[PDB]
Image: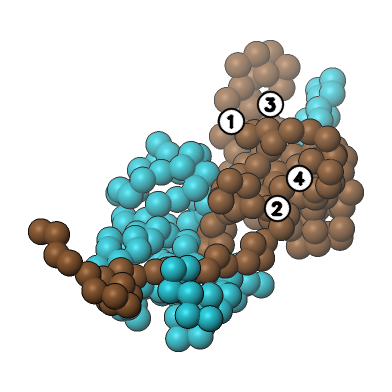
Chain colours: A brown, B cyan
Amino acid sequence: VLRPVLVGGLPGCVNLPSNDDCQCWPLWSSDNAYSFGDVVQQGGVLYTANRDIPPGTPFLAGDWTVYTPGATLVPPHREDASYQQYQAVNFNDKLYTARTDLPPGPFDPANWQEISVEGLVEVADSSTIDFSGDGSASDPLTAAVK
Amino acid sequence: PGCVNLPSNDDCQCWPLWSSDNAYSFGDVVQQGGVLYTANRDIPPGTPFLAGDWTVYTPGATLVPPHREDASYQQYQAVNFNDKLYTARTDLPPGPFDPANWQEISVEGLVEVADSSTIDFSGDGSASDPLTAAVK
């Protein structure tokens, strides 16, 4: 129900928020180059990059990604980023780590650390009859021409 | 200056302050008691500040938390399950684990002791750089 309000009694009947907080994070703008993994605000939501963006491109939704500080991402290998030392990345489903600061370019195994473990490759022979064994017993290529 | 007509100019803060009302999702960041913490699971509103759900935040870190059933995950988020490394295929809602979504495995790359046959030669150890190349 509506009830009167006296003089100066306004603050009791209504409450006011606080002034606007500072935009501590930078603001997206097409006049800036961006490297892999930077941070920007746009429309009240934080975002991060996925590739070296040259200035002038509009805000393509395919480039950026939502930013959630508590997550751990392992993006698939890409031919555009500028990765940092000890940077994780997925290639052909194989984990890897950069060795130094890498400028863009095609994948080059010479610069990426790898972990290794022995395995047991499944083998069938078909027209390469007698394909059998693996690398343990030193018999990975038992096959012969059929 | 007595301007009640206007909102009260308050101090400026650049990190969300915890509350009992705001709903949080796995990974959100809050400021509590002058310290920064991070969520561990989707928290419905009204819950108190249970100490078993918020981890101390340290930006330089890098974590691989165990898989859960009450979390929301983004594409390519990494999780540990049965002592194995998994990565999500697409953003997921809360739910039990299933191989369909998560990347089957993240693996390393084998090595092998090649055998030279009498008809065709073998490769070079199957390492990512020297692929196993055979000739006649």
Q: Earlier in the sequence, mark 4 or mark 3?
A: 4
Do discs 2 and 1 belong to a common subunit? yes
Task: Please say whether residue B96 is visible from this viewpoint.
Answer: yes
Residue occupying image coordinates x 70% and y 52%: A27
Side of B9 relative to B45 (left or right) = right
Picture quadrant where residue A135 is located: top right
User: Which amino acid, by three-letter code, is at mark 3?
Assistant: Ala
Q: Name the residue beneath numbered marker 2.
A: A27
Q: Which residue is mark 3?
A: A143
Question: What is the number of the mark on residue A5?
Answer: none
* Element class at badge 1: loop
Query: Marks 2/4: CA distance?
Result: 6 Å
Closer to the eye: label 1 or 3: 1
Local SS, label 3: loop
Instruction: Name the residue that disc number 4 marks.
Output: A29
**Disc 1 to disc 4, C-alpha distance:** 55 Å
